[PDB]
Image (cartoon, rainbow, N blue to C red; front, side, top):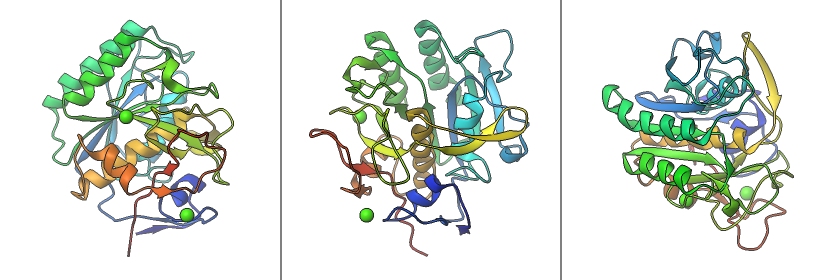
Length: 279
Ligand SMILES: [Ca+2]
Ligand SMILES: [Ca+2]
């Protein structure tokens, strides 16, 4: 399949080179996989989700995404137009309030929730969780992310937007999950992207167009935008049977475009998520 005039990030994950415009992907498109978007919620009614999104848990008064961030991330995972894995099932877990903030205890609880809830869902091709969030280092947040991964969920987390080593942020610094840096359309590390030895992979994160609340769309930037590209890619690859939740991060790294990025500090991987699609 080919989506013409796709958002640059989708084009980039299906090309060995920057600057293309078509997103090439196998039509299976993540069908049969599930992605939990642990964030400010998902506006599931957005037409771009085609009924494939639903809220499954909120830690606040409402499950509505009153912010937009979670809806944006969800759209990069799995919306029709903006999504990597266009046929995946999306499940929203609202751990962040409508200002985009959440206490660590709530974020942990939301991770534990996913680890259990997945057992109640039909996800024959496997389960991914996308965590476009983080704060300062917390062993308890890291341990929650590790548990979620151990439970059989492909966990992708944002590296953070501090232009610093991700070792000082969580859950970015948890080794066992897939920690995602951000790049821009010119294959530079995004100016805000964290870096460091704990990064596993980069994905497109600067000026990413996706869904927004009120049935709208907008372009925003962050490691939060790179993370759902990787989460979506994992779902896509899992549907194709090329990898499993436990191994998807390493598979993505092994099959990534290598050395294409600039302003990568020594010691940080130079790997950009790539679907290796061949018609
Ligand atoms: Ca290249
Ligand atoms: Ca890792």
